Image (tube, rainbow, N blue to C red):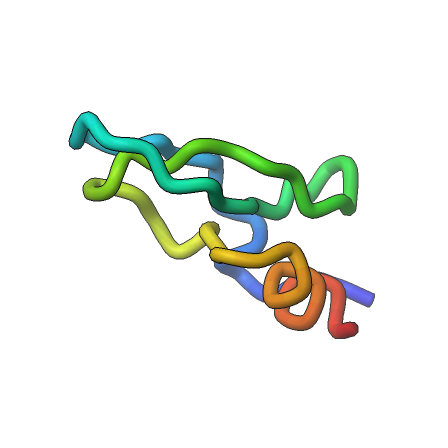
Length: 60
């Protein structure tokens, strides 16, 4: 299995100043991992639940 392109982008908290419990694929660990998204300025490697991160980045 190879993950799609967005699951390999670097985690980016972004430019705003709130918090939003999120998950990203740490593609060199092949795990979904929690992180706090700021609310804006992120990238495509972000998911609200861990399942969605597993569905898309692991093919689950």
